[PDB]
Length: 258
Ligand SMILES: COc1cc2c(cc1OC)[C@@H](C)N(S(N)(=O)=O)CC2
Ligand SMILES: COc1cc2c(cc1OC)[C@H](C)N(S(N)(=O)=O)CC2
Ligand SMILES: [Zn+2]
Image (cartoon, rainbow, N blue to C red; front, side, top):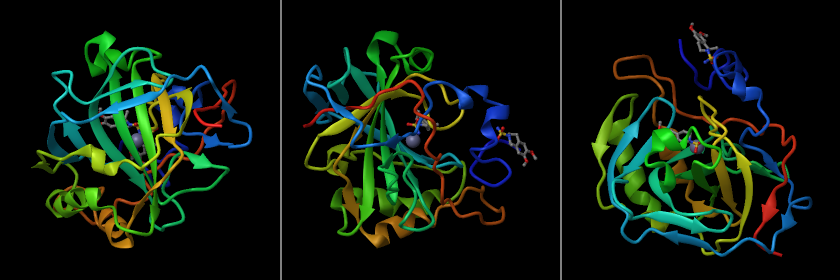
């Protein structure tokens, strides 16, 4: 019926319902590290998550979303390429069926096992639905995951997944601190792009950290036990929920580091 990640409804089909799929600023993209240019005009990046208030985790049939109370100026992203203040609304991941794929952005064509997206909206537009209608409406902080050592700050997420196995299920998810998902370094690449799922709106300033976080094989295996289907339907494992790299077109990727 609707869009997803399969042969018959996956990324290569999305353009029929969402023609912007073939637009001028689509995401993700390949980050060619040799062509990205250091930009001295970039101000320092500010990730201020100390007062973040998580609420709930939801399996939406595409990924799982950890949702935050964004009714107050709490968890915010500022600086870097951004003008003004962007408020955290949710995070989610994209991942693969195997450790050699899963990320949406690639780095010199390298695919990581997964990619975390911390989604923020520009407070100048008042709320998320108005923000996605603007070219500078969203800022998505993207963080690569590689398989190696466990990420202790991820385990609370992993352990709730059994309770939201299928599409439409949610669970209370309070007091989760997203600071535990960040790598040491805030070095990043940035470029103007889009949502990577329908409606594919061209409203995102992408900020993709250079340093991946490490998660354990067991952690990512638990992601792959989720289901795309609803309860009581035949099992379709939630794997390979990533859009591949799209044409860069008339864009430059800027680096925050020399
Ligand atoms: C049977 O019903 C289907 C409905 C749709 C699709 C596939 C289906 O079966 C394969 C995909 C191709 N489009 S979309 N949004 O362009 O990916 C959504 C509508
Ligand atoms: C349905 O809930 C959401 C899903 C998605 C996003 C935000 C959501 O709630 C705010 C953002 C925009 N991503 S992405 N991959 O960072 O571009 C697409 C998927
Ligand atoms: Zn995403």
